[PDB]
Length: 330
Image (cartoon, rainbow, N blue to C red; front, side):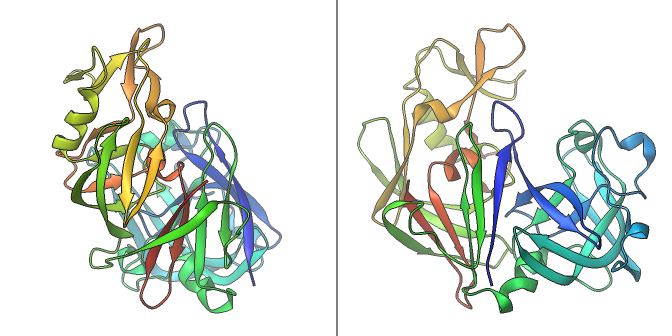
């Protein structure tokens, strides 16, 4: 079996992408953020503190004839400012683009951090990292992809994110009409539970390609591209007037500048990120300073190939017993 669903940017800057997901019987459709950087499927629900819900569509387990409370199970996911989203757990039927999984753990949020409350377009997250990162206690739960793996024609899913445009998540097959040339596959390390791989280098604009190993994670749940300080400094040095700003928390550049492209290596292949993809607009309304899409990972501790990088490619998440990551131009 296979599944296919359209994913849509939530705003004009492509800050995140939402994908409609059917939960329960009869179906309740929520718009979830597909996140290959986490492993929990959690949703706003009828159990969420009513003051923390501001326009989101909520999942109502009492109206689903197939929902079952998972007795004694809880979940808790930690965030940047010490904030956390947490709640209890149900199992229910979950369908993505015609692909149906029964008995999927649906984590119902009892409280969410303010950052999710502020974002009325995201009803929850669907984690697609490896199941060892799932936070359900005392019994860890499997991701949607893990539960679907057996019935999929092929144990893969693909991300085809659009630039200021809709895109596609496919499960169980590789659409050979969605990319050009060949798919280059590269090894994945699962030791930390991420889709972790090693880029073979980078180039800024039409400069020389620099062969250097960059270990990082493919994370559809992160907007920007976070790379080592040496790489990021080399990029922004080519943008006249660009500087690192502590008040803003990253590199800013004059909005009138034209940004060079950024190339990253996948084996012997090269993925080119157009310079327009790196422009994330004014830091505040009316400002002439614009926020950059390539930022330093020094404070993060891990390099993250986020949406800025992934939307420049057709990306295959191959969940075979030896997992790999595929990249193709499109």
